[PDB]
Image (cartoon, coloured by chain):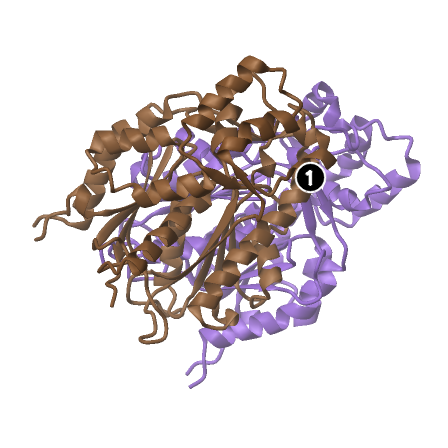
Chain colours: A brown, B purple
Amino acid sequence: RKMERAEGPASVLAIGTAVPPNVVYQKDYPDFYFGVTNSNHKTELKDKFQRMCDKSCVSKRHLYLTEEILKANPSLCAYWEPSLDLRQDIVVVEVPKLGKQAASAAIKEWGQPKSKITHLIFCTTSGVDMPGADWALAKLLGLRSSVKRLVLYMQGCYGGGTVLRIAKDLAENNKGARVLVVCSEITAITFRGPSDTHLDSLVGQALFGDGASALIVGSDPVPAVERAWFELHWTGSDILPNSDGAIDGHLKEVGLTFHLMKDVPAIISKNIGGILKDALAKVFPAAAPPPPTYNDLFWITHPGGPAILDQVEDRLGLRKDKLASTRAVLDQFGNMSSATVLFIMDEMRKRSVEQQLGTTGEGHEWGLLLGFGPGLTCETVVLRSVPLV
Amino acid sequence: RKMERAEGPASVLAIGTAVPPNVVYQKDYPDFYFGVTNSNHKTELKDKFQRMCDKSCVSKRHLYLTEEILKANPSLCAYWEPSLDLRQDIVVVEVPKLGKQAASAAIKEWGQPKSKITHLIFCTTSGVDMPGADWALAKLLGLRSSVKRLVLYMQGCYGGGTVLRIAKDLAENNKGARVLVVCSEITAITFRGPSDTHLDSLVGQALFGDGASALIVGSDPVPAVERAWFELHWTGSDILPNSDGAIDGHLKEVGLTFHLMKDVPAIISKNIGGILKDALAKVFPAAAPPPPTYNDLFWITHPGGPAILDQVEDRLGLRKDKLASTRAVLDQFGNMSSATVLFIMDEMRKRSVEQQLGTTGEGHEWGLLLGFGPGLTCETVVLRSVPLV
């Protein structure tokens, strides 16, 4: 082997997060949104949106777009006005910048010099460019010029699973590799005024927030030097049946536009049990210990919306505390697309340390990270926690 | 290890290619281009473009865009008219379709049923969508719903190296994995009328062609069942010094636009020697056989333009036959962005079989695949050929 491979499982060695400083509380969002888009006269539409926010299970969100920025760029406040060039000019700069803030936090926690990063995966649904956000982030951080980069554009809400799926193989197949994984999402690419033609875009206006998360992933952590928090053990991807057109997203001259053509919560909740039962059977094969029960796993579930969480919890019979870490991130940050599951991973390990639980996964040994997005694609990662003190 | 890994080097087990049926001969292109864009009056500009075509070392190209299609969509023939939505509507369909033709050829050669494909990498610089070209191709082929997909968008001309870099780790770290790798490029995303404001776009009009290439990549080929053609042994990526802005590409409301701000052939040729010397020192370390000389390697070099090839050949002292396979593909297909190096790989193995040479790499054991693109990024892959009969 001309490139030596690693031995142990790919492991999360650090996690950083970053959000835009400007907060909008959900109780204020209907007035803010319909006010800044000159849409207060659309009284019926505004009451529909109010109900959406009331049921969103989102208390606040961090948003790059401020009233000041929107007032300065009225094509963003319009509905269906040509705006892509303006949106790109924003997010091609701001997405790597936010990712840099998260990456610097992860690197500081990790403790090694930044030149030990050998690989970079940058995932975003906000903007595209050449060179890409991966190159821009490498420049902002001053990574080695020979860092092996990969940019994952237009991924959508399953991308947090995808980056782990890829980072697993990069770390395990390359001795000494240390992979910087960044997911950065900024809703300036999709923000638009309200319309009763496109009630789909209203859902996103209630749920989507901004944020970036960064990991250091590597195999064979140096004893007493690096610290593993979660291990990546099994990965799977599935296109769910009868889901054509469930979630479409098009990059148009008016920006990024989303379309929901099917009952996404019903498709996810109806199919997830068989996916997880299969995954757990592969990880714990009979020939031998049986799979843990769902209530004895920890759960890092992409919170696409509250209905997905409610219907998954109901269909699988999950105890009401299993999705608590997931719901906490949804409540405080909204749906941050691909970045969200890494925020939940951070929330979970932090709660576990603070409450002196016996593992980084809320006291459980094994766990599941799930991403859902266009496809309809389900990304499944089986994780192992690490024991605490 | 909950997912068993493979043992041997990631190997190319099959290669397919596909091009649009419509051919434009370079001798005809100046009249065709300036005629279809209502630009024959721009006499000085047309003579500049004629000289570019005369020096291009491209004899013909395959192009999706025909006179009939251009006549039906005049915004494509204009210069700097809003056109992105139209271009996307085309390439979001035609890029996966062309990739399907190449993938079916590779699968037929491979000989295994298509459901043995476990992973898919789809690389394109032409269009973006959600779900992406990877999903569309999986649908067109009828791959397994659980195929592990990755879409590499807005890569540019280094992408043929990138896909091998990634496919190497997917194949080697997953026992039984068989990776379908597709690069598909269609210039409808960048085609625009001529302007003396943007002489950069004229270069692309002389050189860029359409095409798709597909590989099956896997470790541990089944003896007497699967056939290895090349082995992937070492990979490297470098951002070349003093190359900021050398190649920029922006997805705008007028489509994809390229900008060349530095002497790309000089930057590549001045830096490539140190990159290759380092790579070969890593593959053949002293502690032991010395690296082959450049003339005893086979060369699969992205032909970004004839000046890159001429200056690399001159600076490295390459014998004039070393780049023959590379120049043959440039001559017959033009620069097909990320797909081009896989066409060259196919041309080289086919010539080697036809001429009864002793290896798939023109009789040489070791070789180099080089991609160059925005960054300025250089992707280096050290390859081993396979002995023939």
Q: Using residue B329 as the reference point, say whether residue A247 is left or right of it.
A: left
Q: Residue A156 at x, y = what percent?
A: 47, 38
Q: Quadrant of residue A316?
A: top left
Q: Can the viewer see residue B65 in this picture?
A: no
User: Relative to B65, does residue A108 appear above or below in the rendering?
Assistant: below
Q: Residue B15 at x, y = what percent?
A: 44, 46
Q: Can the viewer see residue B297 in this picture?
A: yes
Give the number of marks: 1
The residue at the point 70 percent across, 29 percent down is A75
The residue at the point 64 percent across, 23 percent down is A79
Secondary structure at badge 1 equals: helix
Q: Using residue B166 as the reference point, say whether residue A241 is left or right of it.
A: left
**Quarter the N terminus of chain B occupies:** bottom left
Residue A349 vs residue B303, the one in the foreground: A349
In the current view of this chain or complex, which residue is farthest to the top?
A: A44
In the current view of this chain or complex, which residue is farthest to the left?
A: A287
Q: Quadrant of residue A218?
A: bottom left
**Quarter the C terminus of chain B occupies:** bottom left
User: Relative to B281, does residue B312 appear above or below in the rendering?
Assistant: above
Q: Quadrant of residue B107?
A: top left
Q: Please, what is the three-letter code of the amino acid marked with disc 1? A: Ile
Chain bearing mark 1:
A
Q: Residue A239 at x, y = what percent?
A: 35, 33
Judge the density around disc 1: few (<14), some (14-19), many (≥20) Cα neighbours within 10 Å. Answer: few
* Disc 1 target residue: A69
Residue A95 vs residue B253, the one in the foreground: A95
The residue at the point 50 percent across, 50 percent down is A212
Q: Residue A136 at x, y = what percent?
A: 61, 55
